[PDB]
Image (cartoon, rainbow, N blue to C red; front, side, top):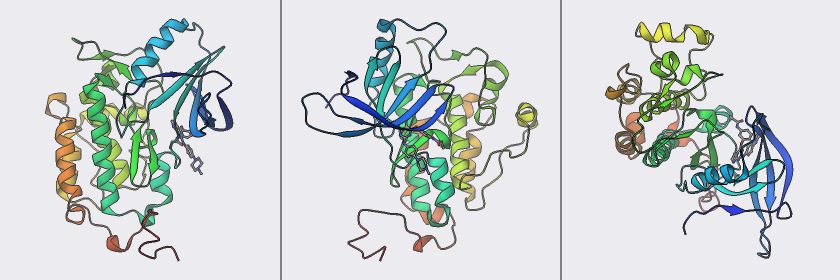
Length: 302
Ligand SMILES: *CCC(=O)Nc1cccc(Oc2nc(Nc3ccc(N4CCN(C)CC4)cc3)nc3[nH]ccc23)c1
């Protein structure tokens, strides 16, 4: 029904193994066995790094209630929290990992229908975040996760920020940033908006359409703002029709107001997803197959 934050005790879940780690902390594959409920639920557990100045439990719970309220099919949901000496966030497990690695591993069998459906889903998730006044600030194929080959979800590792009712921008402080996914105004001035998220969406789409290529490969991050100001952009992927590439280019306009809105991106990519082979040209497209629950019905995977 309605998405609410569950408070878990250490007795109710178990970390099984490490999946990955970063500045944020460590993420584990885990099991949630809710007290009294007699059910066992695979989950992802994020145990956050110990901060120099740990927030009070009250502060943490307030933030967690807001993040738990984020409830959309294409955003990975926070299911519960456990506060002890550490903060552990219990998330939906996305069994197939990140979309970036998925498209690199399965590129020989990824057709136009899947690529365009993923673009739609990511746009829907981002539009929902915008409706919630959340600026993501790290959208990229590595941060979209795969529930099934047919269904992906945007995830957040701590960079997302909630804007106030009258705030149209987040002003960031120093630190490491994903330069090659960022809008010019973010690179130069540390300014983030829903429209700088749109820039990152464009780069994410480019990643997908090149089956996981690195943007501006071999170019130093420090040179990126210079090339953008000269007007250079990521090139047309070979499988993309001009129509698709033009949407992507609109995401990278210098004037943030000239970029598309996520609501518009949903409409345009939804149109294309309805006739995928008109908009993406992939050799052997009609023959390509990814694992689907209908495989048995159609006698695939013999
Ligand atoms: C491309 C970016 C990347 O590798 N992302 C990533 C790695 C590890 C954990 C993580 O956070 C969450 N992961 C999952 N599910 C998950 C992760 C990894 C894997 N496997 C796939 C197969 N390869 C060979 C090894 C790794 C399987 C499932 N679910 C989550 N829910 C919330 C956060 C995460 C992201």
